[PDB]
């Protein structure tokens, strides 16, 4: 049923969700708690939404998956100031994501 990249993409998403820096990114921001978030961030993304999209076969290539992961990290660095804790968390999680990708032989063509 799923395409050839599904197992490694689920492995990567599992790695992301289990990383110690991932907590701020596990679920969508709640507008009831952060009133201006969806005025600032036009294309929101989070790891639970990525999980649902992966299940629905929206990621055919690692490139499709990485584009959504980049939204997670870039949105966080747009909303939060440089050098603040959440910007640092986004930097740490993105760096970890790329360490994991570089370890997958079939994904050697990919680069940040």
Image (tube, rainbow, N blue to C red):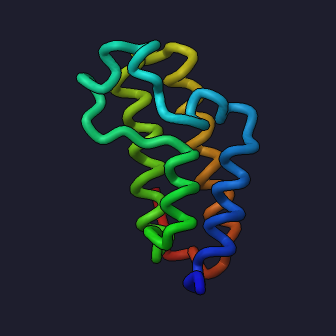
Query: Depth check: 95 or 9 in front?
Result: 9
Q: Residue at x 44, y 69 (%)?
A: 58
Instruction: Name the quadrant of the N terminus.
Output: bottom right
x, y percent for residue 34: 41, 14
Q: Residue at x 68, y 74 (%)?
A: 7
Q: Residue at x 50, y 41 (%)?
A: 46
Viewed as shown, does residue 68 lie left or right of 85?
left
x, y percent for residue 104: 67, 72
With respect to residue 5, does 83 lie above or below?
above
x, y percent for residue 10: 66, 64
With respect to residue 66, does 84 lie above or below?
above
Residue 53 visible somewhere in the drawing: yes
Viewed as shown, does residue 58 lie left or right of 11?
left
Residue 91 visible somewhere in the drawing: no
With respect to residue 16, does 79 lie above or below?
above
Label total for image: 0
x, y percent for residue 78: 34, 26
User: Which residue of the protein is positioned furthest toward the front in this rendering?
Assistant: 32
Q: Residue at x 61, y 81 (%)?
A: 106
């Amino acid at each position: 049923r799923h395409g050839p990249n599904y197992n490694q993409l689920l492995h990567l998403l599992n790695d992301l969700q289990n990383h110690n820096s991932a907590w701020p990114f596990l679920v969508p921001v709640n507008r009831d708690d952060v009133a201006d978030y969806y005025d600032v961030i036009k294309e929101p993304m989070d790891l639970s939404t990525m999980e649902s999209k992966l299940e629905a076969d929206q990621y055919l290539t690692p490139e499709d998956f990485i584009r959504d992961a980049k939204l997670v990290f870039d949105n966080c660095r747009k909303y939060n100031n440089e050098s603040t804790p959440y910007a640092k968390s986004a930097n740490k999680l993105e760096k970890f994501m790329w360490q994991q990708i570089k370890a997958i032989p079939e994904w050697s063509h990919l680069e940040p």
